[PDB]
Length: 45
DNA sequence: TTTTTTTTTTTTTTTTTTTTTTTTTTTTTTTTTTTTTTTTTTTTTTTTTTTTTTTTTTTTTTTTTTTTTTTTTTTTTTTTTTTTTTTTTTTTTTTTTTTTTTTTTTTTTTTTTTTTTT
Image (cartoon, rainbow, N blue to C red; front, side, top):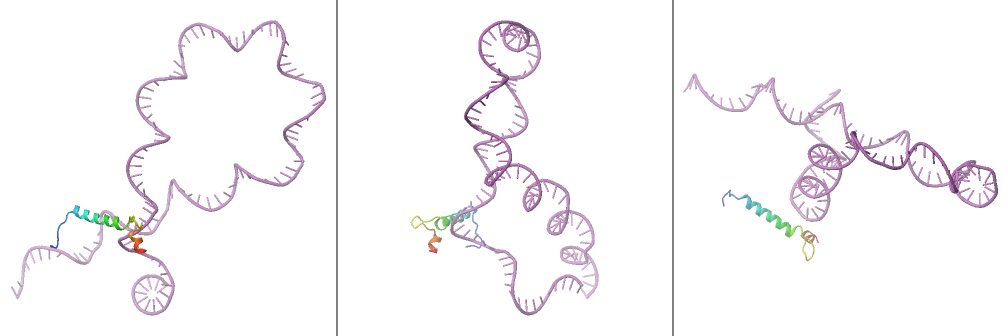
């Protein structure tokens, strides 16, 4: 691995935004259908 | 060993621009002054029977000047076009909801030092 390794802006943007979007969708905002709680409520309880 | 070329930051102080303190004009805001509404009671006004002498409408006839009337030529009415205003689709922007990422301030208390004023 070199000190500097070029990366396309499209791939970096796609990877970063998809990681953030999937993380939010799966574990910040929507509730689970079974227990009806977000991860915040589950962890607090 | 002496002597010669070049390079920049300072003696800089002045020109240009920027920043920061100012105060005229149309849009708010508190006051006094004039329009509204509900009670008391109060002499006062006003609703309803009886009698009465009145003065205007309906028998009948008359005319004349407003109702008949026809026609010329105007002139208001209608047509087209275009501009001005009103009104409603369209678009844009902003706010709130709930989990996330980030920050930012005001005062007590004592003791010692800078930092201005007299």
